[PDB]
Length: 207
Image 1: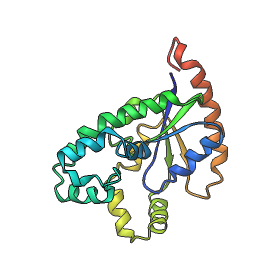
Image 2: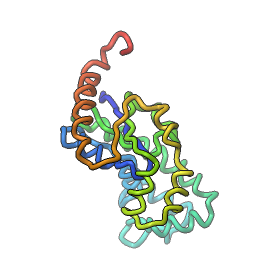
Image 3: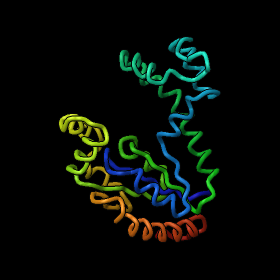
Image 4: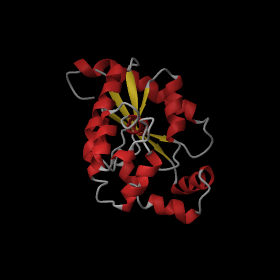
């Protein structure tokens, strides 16, 4: 049984930067997006039901998914998008706990961009939020993606607010100024998490 520390943050908060810092400390990272990408890769059951629902030509000859192609027709008929979820959802769910169970580190870092939006913090033991100013969010996204300021702002208005994230955070790490000052905080958090991880299974009283 692994202690699950969930990580989340808005677009451009540098989630990857924080996750890698924990990775360097020996923690296994389970990214929610990679999980989502794997359940629809060659061999996966999800490919099948896709061909049965949307169509046979949904899956290329080499068995791989026409990922960027499917993403089109779905947003062309967004009412099926909900369907394409009841299918992948339980699978994502299964793969995620399968990889939590496979981790050997004292605790795992579960990076969930939509932690707040999908209330996935209800499945975490600890919630770490990487926090930055909305300004920084705009800045970094206007460079790493080459988009207008009103394009990112349009995204921000679609994700949970900064405050909504802080409302469910157990720990918060500041990341709006050089991916190096992070070292200090991660080390602190990491030390505490090991502490929590080693005691949670047999702890008689909360905290």
